[PDB]
Structures are given as C-alpha cells and as structure tokens.
Length: 226
Image: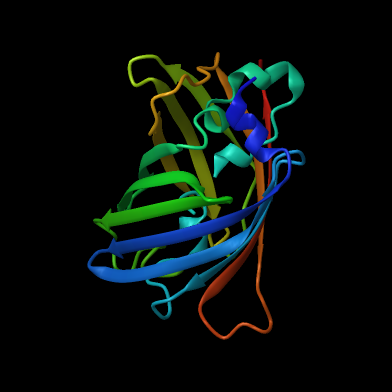
C-alpha cells in the first residue's frame, strides 16, 4: 500500500524519450502510448527519429516502466515502483550481450503532469560490427521472462536481475544479461520488497501506416513469487 499506487488505478498516458549512441552511432527514439496497471498492460508505439536504427528494435525493449506491473493484492507491499511515485525513480542498467558489446543506461521515470515519463540515455560499446547486433541478425520477436527483484536498503531501492533471450535468425538464441538498479528520486518513504519477480511477456508488431523506423509494442506484466 502506497499513495503512489493511487496514481495508477486508471489508464495512464505514457511518454518515452531515448537518446543513444552505439559504437558512435547516434540515434533517438520517441514512444507514446498508455499503461493500465490493473491489467498489467502497456501499449506503446516507438518511433526512430533518426532514421534507420543502428541496432535492432528488440535490443531496446528493456530499456524502452515497470511501475505499470500488475501487483496482486497479497503483494501490494512489494511494489517499490509505484511507491516512488510521483517523484519517480532513476533506473540504470548494464546490459551484456554474450560475445558482443554492451549497453549502459540511465533513465528517469516520473510523472510529468498526468503523463508518466520515461527519459533515457543509452551508451553502447564494443559491438562486433558484423555481430548479431550490428548485423541486425535478430528476429523481430520477443519471449516472456522473469525479472527478479530484491530490496537494496542502502540504495534505498532495489536491485534487479534477469537474462533476456533474443531469438537469432540462424535459429540460435543470443543472451542479454541484465543488471539493474533503481532508486527513488524523491524523499518520501518507498516500499522495499521481499524478494520477488515480475512475469513479463511482450509482442512486437508494425504500423502499416507508418513510414519511419518503428516498433509497435504490447506487453503484459504481473508480479509473483512471494
């Protein structure tokens, strides 16, 4: 239970802005959409504003609002994300794609007025040029996964972990090992959960009326494990 929680009882409009630079390649992405935590549902649409993306759409999914996760009642006390609202939280990650480069990200998620805003910068290095990433060798798809959460009393927030399995055109799968940390931007109290995870599924598609490089995303998230 948290006041922040009261901010997500309805459908909330979403804002997404990303500035990134991978192996010097620069780009920007914008997303608009809405979230319905009651159903743990996200529906967003992403647009490249800088032309054909240097990396695949699927590698940016993680980066591109866990506060929209559906917390069943018996877990309401474990919802750091909502509790940090409206002030928000900073979400930082280091993502390692096996046998390739890595992304380092930092973002701020908070309300801006009535819109929940996800503001991110990303920096990627070491990609192998003809690698699955620079190679655009991944399938435009996505698996369900479990995101593990635990409290970080010293950070006054959480420590998050998981491993993304990206399907590869040759029928192989490439791993994107995720390390994440979240901390409150604000100074009010937050919920510091016992250990748990989020059951997450995403489905990507495309907008037939859309000319720019883009991604249509639908995602369902529900907390479990306590």
